Image (cartoon, rainbow, N blue to C red; front, side, top):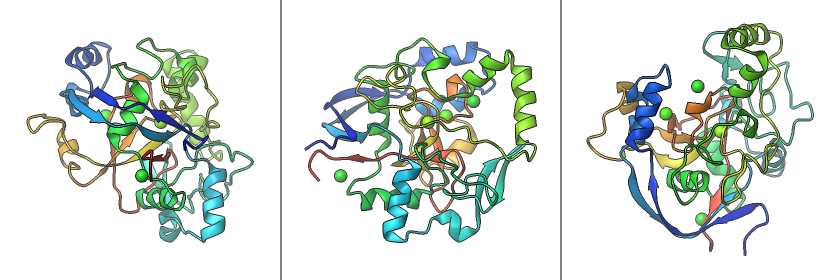
Length: 292
Ligand SMILES: [Ca+2]
Ligand SMILES: [Cl-]
Ligand SMILES: [Cl-]
Ligand SMILES: [Mg+2]
């Protein structure tokens, strides 16, 4: 019935999105991003779902390599010659970056095959799920699995704990101030062959886990959903760059090792170009109906 590597999310009706008092609170917690960077989570909406299955972990390097080994699959990033990595200053195209060269030519997996696979395009993700006899999760399925049957900021509750997940809150906390974290980000990314900052799937289990058992629904890597970017209501108004991708980008969830706490909440929405774009911080996990 239920594959040992998935968990059953019980059917029910939940409130998708984030309430006004949460947005107010993001205003007040000295967050850079203005209010209209979070309004795409609003208004909350009643979403009804059946029981459904979702992977416990993100797809690992090792699992994707089995897919590639058996099928010969070639990823978008390999056909293009490159993929995106965040450099010293901004996002950059890195020649040779792909799932097995996560920092480009001169890098490799180096025994980190229990980490989530990255440089996965939307089509790379859909193809692996087909092969596995599964699919991507919808955004609704993803958020439900993350927040639980009632609303909460992070999968473990409403109180932040940098020890519960792979985010930049841990690393900045360890370096002592936000100055020292910027100075660090400099010194590592200055060529210096950037050490990967992903973590093995399930490394922060069980403390970081969601109520239903999903691991790493916070931080580590961004995750594709199958959902086409859409507003929760026709009157929602966000930053123009967000309307620009409405109706064409696919929703990306969960934040990444690079994010701080406000960009890795259960309800946070990101968006990605589904036509052969990928980056070194973006992977996925699968879902499935209870009955294929
Ligand atoms: Ca967002
Ligand atoms: Cl952030
Ligand atoms: Cl299915
Ligand atoms: Mg994530």
